[PDB]
Amino acid sequence: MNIFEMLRIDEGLRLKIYKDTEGYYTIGIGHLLTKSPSLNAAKSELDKAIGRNTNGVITKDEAEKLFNQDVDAAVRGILRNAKLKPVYDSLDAVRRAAAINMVFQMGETGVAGFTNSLRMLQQKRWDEAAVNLAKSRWYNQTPNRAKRVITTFRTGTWDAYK
Ligand SMILES: [Ar]
Ligand SMILES: [Ar]
Ligand SMILES: [Cl-]
Ligand SMILES: [Cl-]
Image (cartoon, rainbow, N blue to C red; front, side):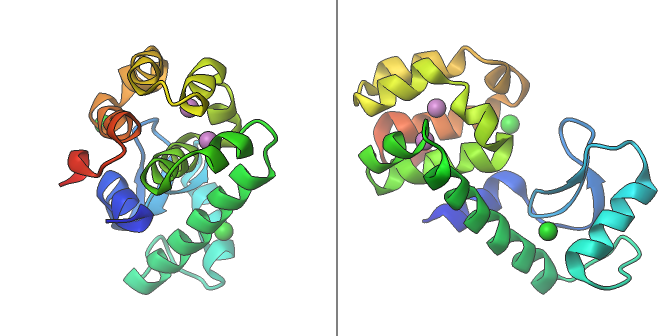
């Protein structure tokens, strides 16, 4: 297992524009298009992203290409964030993938807001971190996914995904 497989399980794959858990227009493997309530606006953003007149539909390869860029951007966003980078560098491989999933889902910004959890992960206090991470809107709104990511940080293994 790895980051790609992990996120492919959490996000799914859809080839037509859809609304995510927050009601935002998305396509592919969790590629958010826009926070706007306009379907047209989402179609405009999709065309621009792909570089062709898609009409709300893409191929598997295009979805996978967006996905690669989004993983890459997430990692780079972590590395560029003063609050995140040090946490990240302190973690082992498995846990790093848990950190990436979270940023992919909620943005750098969002993640950089779990100050307390961040600190406990940096100190390797796994159980305490797991409990603090669960005290969040993230967990209350997408409890199944959150539990998988949380178990990942807790144990450092991929059992939640196997
Ligand atoms: Ar992180
Ligand atoms: Ar975190
Ligand atoms: Cl894009
Ligand atoms: Cl969920």
